[PDB]
Amino acid sequence: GASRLYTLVLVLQPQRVLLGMKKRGAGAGRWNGFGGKVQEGETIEDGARRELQEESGLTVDALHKVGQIVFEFVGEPELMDVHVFCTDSIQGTPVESDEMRPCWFQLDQIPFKDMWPDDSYWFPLLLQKKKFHGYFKFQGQDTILDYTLREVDTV
Ligand SMILES: Nc1nc2ncccc2[nH]1
Image (cartoon, rainbow, N blue to C red; front, top):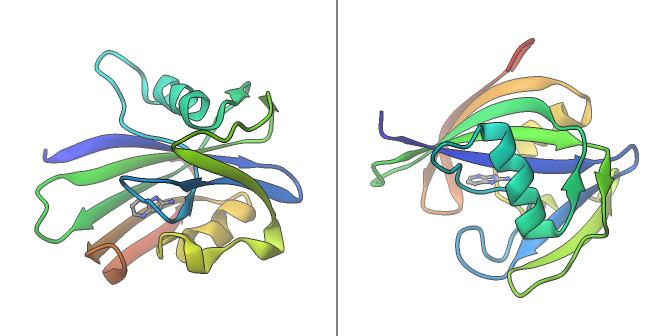
């Protein structure tokens, strides 16, 4: 249907959240959660666990579905269908790699100015343990043309 599955994992603990600064490629220069494309024959949740490991070095125990966000970029045919998960139970220490620099942020110091602009809209919901369905239409990397965002009981 001209949509591609992605995952996004937020390691969200009671007073802090882990974010990674991407060194190059999609989302370079921004703090973001950990995720990527889902593979053939892989469940979305299994893909989320794999991407968390690949990008942050962390092994997640329990993962919970928190949202689904569809991203449209004008002029690009494929919609990004992003399945968002959160966890507080992880193992390992975050690893800085060529591709990603990890840092913990206190919740009142989340660096929204250095994040994708849609984050400002749906992070308030994530932090209050709400679940959501969102859609954001972007022109380029920086401008939200329009959006919808609603809370839901089931993702
Ligand atoms: N956290 C996050 N926000 C995003 N917005 C647009 C594309 C990818 C994104 N990842």
